[PDB]
Amino acid sequence: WAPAIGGEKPSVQQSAKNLPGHTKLKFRQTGQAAEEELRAKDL
RNA sequence: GACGAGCUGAACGCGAAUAUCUCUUUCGCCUUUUACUAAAGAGAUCCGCGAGUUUUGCUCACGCAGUCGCAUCUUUUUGUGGGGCU
């Protein structure tokens, strides 16, 4: 009938799924549809 | 034309030692979840580690000092001299 609304010291409990991982982002390079590469062509 | 041991800082980098975890999958335990198995991958973490001057702490030490702004017989520094012609 009505869901829970999810509004937002800090607690020091550390989850296992919250440990560092995939700590850098991949960006699209030349050759993977990067934005500056794709203005150049007629799609 | 010339001199370090120990600690914390460095900011850059992974000889031989290696454990844990997370995720995405498969496989096996198999009632369920933990807790596990063993494969494929993708990611972290731990415990450590090397060099640059920063000096803190020596308990060592220094300056007419090791170095300064190849030395007479045929092939090299002991030259073959002197004159004069267009």
Image (tube, coloured by chain):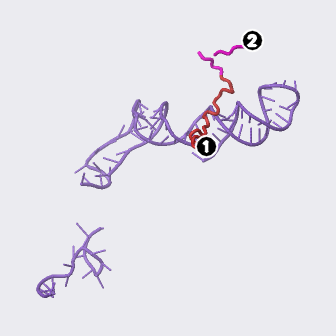
Chain colours: A red, B purple
Dot 1 falls on which chain? A
Q: Residue A37, how many percent across, how many down?
A: 58, 42
Q: Amino acid at mark 1?
A: Asp
Residue A11 drawn above or below residue B1? above
Q: Which residues are magenta?
A: A2-13
Q: Quadrant of residue A22?
A: top right
State the residue at coordinates (68%, 16%).
Answer: A6
State the residue at coordinates (57%, 40%).
Answer: A39
In the rendered image, residue A21 lying in the magenta stretch gets the answer no
Residue B7 drawn above or below residue B1? above
Q: Residues within 10 Å of mark 2 (few under 14, many from 20)?
A: few
Q: Amino acid at mark 2?
A: Ala
- Tell me the SS state at disc 2: loop
Which mark is first along the chain, 1 or 2? Answer: 2
Q: Residue B80, how many percent across, how many down?
A: 20, 81
Q: Quadrant of residue B60?
A: top left
State the residue at coordinates (56%, 40%).
Answer: A36
- Left/right of residue A20 with respect to residue B26 in the rendered view: left
Residue A42: assigned label: 1
Q: Nearer the viewer, residue A13 or B68?
A: A13
Q: Quadrant of the C terminus of chain A?
A: top right
Q: Residue B18, how many percent across, how many down?
A: 68, 39
Give the residue at mark 2.
A2
Q: Quadrant of the N terminus of chain A?
A: top right
Q: Nearer the viewer, residue B83 or A30?
A: A30
In the rendered image, residue A4 lying in the magenta stretch gets the answer yes
